[PDB]
Length: 380
Ligand SMILES: Cc1cc2cc(c1)C(=O)N[C@H]([C@H](O)CNC(C)(C)c1ncc(C(C)(C)C)o1)COC/C=C/CCCC2=O
Image (tube, rainbow, N blue to C red; front, side, top):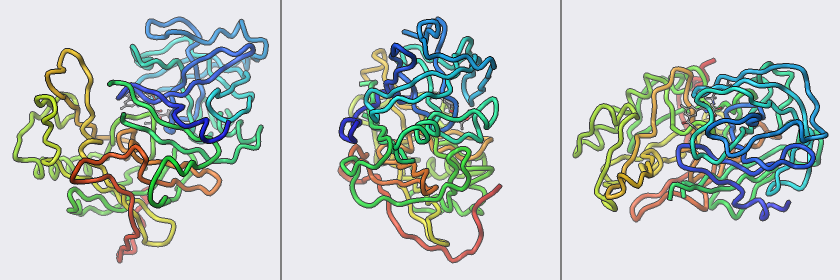
């Protein structure tokens, strides 16, 4: 249960989430569970499905307790429905503890489970305010903290790592071997999603020049369950215009910028240097101070592994328009060590031990930056 024994406890397939091994029930039933900072329900496949290798069999668990209540969660992509109950849960490569937690037993779903993803359930790590059916359903992490001495903090090192990816979820603390340089903290604005505030956006150091509330219209969040960086429409359009300008020595079809169509180069020849760096400036812990996190094209051009196209390297543009605020998804978290410091209501970013670099540019977390304008960047 030591932090070192938690290193490398995550696996995934690119664009399909990262998952940790758990057990549910007595005796323990092993399942792989997607780690989601963008939701707050713990839910597991509990009936057969074409894409599930295995599923939770409540009838084999003596500790299962039925709560006699249904529950439905509609995600941005995918949805499921099922029955609530509680059971014992453990994380074999997490802390050394067993807790009783709410579990939604999924009995019907649509476009939620993913063919070949290797996971069978979801661990929503965000706060009760966004749990279904309502905020009286205590989330898993709340139960863990209440029932054990685990400190109220976890960290995620998602590695873009050949379709297979890895990383680490450190429960209850911060493992200094997983990052270099300083950790910079941004405040959690409200405990529902992991809501943060972006104060500035640059593309190859050119400010997008918008009122900073636009960046957080109508919230900005850190979400390991969404793949892409998602940007409010107005911000999205300004960003795409600036990235197109920076990369204009090559022209790509509209479908590529819509994040729908692949772009392919002969293997080993991807022209990284024509694509700009994106800087996201996060509110700091002191008034009108910020820090920035810098994203390279190796993070926002997501490779799509496919043997059939493997004479080439092919990528999707991993930035999408949103109508529900900014989503700093997995492609933004990859190569940073991200500390979800619930105890101190803040989120820490540092350059990860698995960072993106090439011979010219390196992903960075740096600061402080000061801004003269006294405007509050929070929208809501
Ligand atoms: C646009 C989008 C893409 C994808 C998933 C998603 C979206 C997606 O919806 N991911 C899920 C994550 O919980 C979504 N988080 C936000 C956007 C905050 C959200 N929307 C709705 C909610 C409530 C739960 C509060 C009702 O929260 C997690 O799903 C499992 C992850 C699978 C891997 C990513 C697969 C993917 O391609």
